[PDB]
Image 1 (spheres, one colour):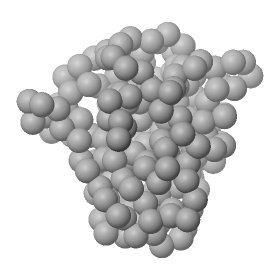
Image 2 (cartoon, one colour):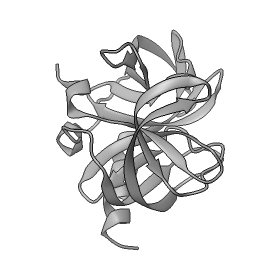
Image 3 (tube, helix red, strand yellow):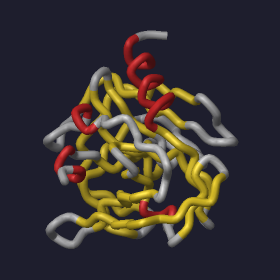
Image 4 (cartoon, helix red, strand yellow):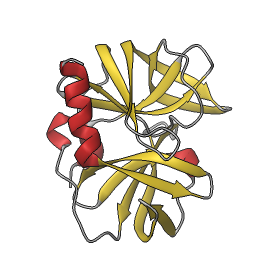
Length: 182
């Protein structure tokens, strides 16, 4: 409808795949080359389904901060025959608050879904499903099951992936440029 949704659409059309693990179907954001991210609670194994095709996982790393606290981001390298468009220049460098964010989801259940979630708070610490978690972003939308892995964007930035909600607020794990230097 407007330039928020325009940036979100451009990320979804080129930089997302449907990932299926034994824990369900997730929106998966491709970042560069064969490297993608998914919430750690997807429990990625040796094999994953990508757009319903059996795919070997070459590497999977569940990120933690330097205090050994969960960040709820898994970086996955896929044995895929195609690279993602490099979107690392759209990643923030520092922890921050944001105006006017969109949460975008693409699954079997929720195809081409875009939610204007509005203002995003640097929440920091959250007890997420009983796990102490850092670098959490919070928005006031009553987000539901099937939105995990959803991409959170502003105009010009990819700031996080949806990892949970409490019926009133949604929670995203931060994406930082420094996760994907190589």
